[PDB]
Image: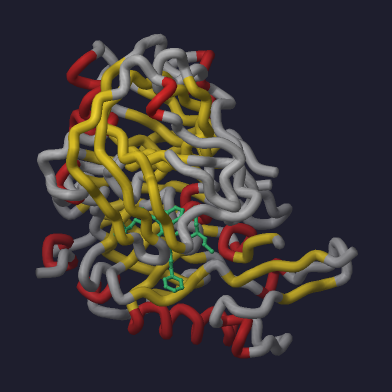
Amino acid sequence: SFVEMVDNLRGKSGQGYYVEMTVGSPPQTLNILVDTGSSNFAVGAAPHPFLHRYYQRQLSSTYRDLRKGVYVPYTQGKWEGELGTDLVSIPHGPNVTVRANIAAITESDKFFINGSNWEGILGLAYAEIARPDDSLEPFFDSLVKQTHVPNLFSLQLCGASVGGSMIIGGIDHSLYTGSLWYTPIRREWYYEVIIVRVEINGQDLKMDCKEYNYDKSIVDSGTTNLRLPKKVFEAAVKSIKAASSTEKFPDGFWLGEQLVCWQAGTTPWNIFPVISLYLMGEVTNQSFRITILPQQYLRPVQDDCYKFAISQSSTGTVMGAVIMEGFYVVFDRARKRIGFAVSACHVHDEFRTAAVEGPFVTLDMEDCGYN
Ligand SMILES: CCCC(CCC)S(=O)(=O)C[C@@H](NC(=O)OCc1ccccc1)C(=O)N[C@@H](Cc1ccccc1)[C@H](O)CNCc1cccc(OC)c1
């Protein structure tokens, strides 16, 4: 826990959450995007049309070239650069400094966002998925080995300019309500979790739970949308369309292309269903569920306009930022589990409310994992 980290995140809708950091000696200040979806710490180290500032290794008396190149291809977007180490600090985070690996981005393609206000990315996932390989120790691992910071972190992403919190090394009880529920981390590469059941407005999607994790399911703060495997994505949309069949929208809308708008304050929330994702529990045949309100999957962009924030994937399910916004998520690395609880900045609806409920019986949860 810690008072000093409570409102340490910012960013605008659909463009990621970032924390302030400093690299080099003297300290160079940079806004770094918090990404539990990757494992590389990387910062712009050269001019780019979208960067307002960048890491200047020549001005840091502590920079050390590892004389190895590196590149990372993301779902959408990629960068190239040079590996080296330097001292790093999180002003509104723990009170320590550590020497961490840093990828000085020299070239990039569809990575940096125009007007996002962040110049780097902090991959908080495990080494197993780092570039060039798992031998490049991720930032957090370094932080944990060099300091006393406990091996754990929590994220409170709030919807809207946007804000939130990253509690390095603990859980701040003032950021959530109710009980914290934990789902195991299936394997330590991405923050993989196993989905056991899916319901739209109470109706079971009735699919083979293996489909929910076809390939895999991960908790990715680096991704905006809820990403679903083809088959699941088609079932969901079909169900969501029917629920709101009272009104008609263009195919481009469901594809995430063109947005939809309603006269200010007249958004028909009631016609959009809630989605419940049941996750594997900590006890035998026991699971729990988190419920997403349409306010979460209809991202805001005169009138009120929104973008359907659920899209199909060919790389498994991705519990993106919109899924995380209604809750307080605990990345308990130390106990290989992830916790969910209603967030202090929860979403609102006079008649409906996002939730984290348990316990639930769910037989054969193991058969839900993909192989
Ligand atoms: C900040 C939110 C940007 C969105 C809005 C853009 C209009 S996004 O689009 O949701 C970002 C997503 N992109 C996305 O979801 O793209 C979908 C898409 C749309 C159109 C065409 C192709 C793909 C994504 O790639 N995220 C990675 C972080 C990142 C941050 C900022 C810029 C580029 C990347 C994250 O690390 C991926 N974690 C799984 C992963 C996957 C593969 C290899 C990995 O390496 C360890 C790891």
Q: Indicate left or right for 73 with 249 as reference.
A: left
Q: Is residue 168 above or below residue 201?
A: above
Q: How many marks?
A: 0
Task: Tell me the quarter of the picture where residue 285 sits.
Answer: bottom left
Residue at the image point whose x is 23% and y is 21% from the top:
144
Q: Quadrant of residue 66?
A: top left
Q: How is the image coloured?
A: secondary structure
Across and down, in percent, residue 115 comes to 65, 50
User: Could you tell whether 263 is left or right of 190 in the image?
Assistant: right
Q: In the displayed structure, would residue 219 be above or below residue 152?
A: below
Residue 322 point in image, percent of width and height = 52, 55
Q: Quadrant of ligand 1?
A: bottom left
Q: Is residue 14 left or right of residue 303?
A: left
Horizontal side, residue 67 vs residue 4: left or right: left
* Residue at image coords 39%, 19%: 60
Is residue 311 something that shows in the picture? yes
> Does residue 291 appear in the picture of this structure?
no
Q: Is residue 101 above or below residue 96?
A: below
Viewer-proximal residue among 348 and 287 = 348
Task: Pick the residue in front: 116 or 268.
Answer: 116
Farthest front residue? 58
Residue drawn at the location 63% of the way across and 62% of the way down? 299
Place of residue 344 in the rendered image (x, y in percent of width and height, measured from the top left): 58, 34
In this rendered view, identify the residue nearer to me: 149 or 346. 149
Quadrant location of the N terminus in the rendered image: top left
Q: Is 147 situated above or below 206? A: above
Residue 328 locus on image (x, y percent) = 46, 38
Q: Residue at x 46, y 17 (%)?
A: 27
Q: State which quarter of the image contains the C terminus.
A: bottom left
